[PDB]
Amino acid sequence: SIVRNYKPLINRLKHYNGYDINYISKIG
Amino acid sequence: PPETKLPYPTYWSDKKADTDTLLYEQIIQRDKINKYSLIRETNGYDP
Amino acid sequence: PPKPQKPVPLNVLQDQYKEGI
């Protein structure tokens, strides 16, 4: 027998406030 | 023990609600929510 | 026939088993 483990979700922040402001700032 | 796909999320806690099972429910529900909202957060709907 | 059971935190499961699983 083997156990099936579900490991919860750990994430790093992708955007700053829903947006990535580096690219937005370039284009702006 | 073959896979069974886990019917409706609160399936477990409806039988002898415990602390660990309730924490598990909360965790999986918020994980689904987070994933879907992130996918819609950056991209958006099909239209 | 090993019927499935409700989930428990991993540490308590691997400790109760006491065998490398």
Image (cartoon, coloured by chain):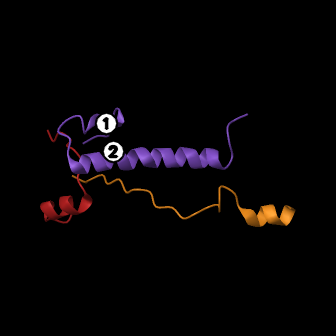
Residue at numbered disc 1: B10
Residues marked 1 and 2 touching at CB (< 8 Å): yes
Residue at numbered disc 2: B25
Residue B3 location in percent, x, y?
32, 40
- In the shown orientation, is residue A24 left or right of residue A7? right
In the rendered picture, chain A carries what hue?
orange
Q: Nearer the viewer, residue B10 or A18?
A: A18
Q: Which chain is red?
A: C
Q: Amino acid at mark 2?
A: Glu
* Numbered disc 1: secondary structure: helix
Residue A4 location in percent, x, y?
30, 52
Sequence-wise first label, 1 or 2: 1
* Numbered disc 2: secondary structure: helix
Identity of the residue drawn at 57% across and 63% down:
A13
Q: Is residue A7 visible?
A: yes
B27 w.r.t. B6: above or below: below
Q: Amino acid at mark 1?
A: Thr
Name the mark on residue A6.
none
Identity of the residue drawn at 76% across and 67% down:
A22
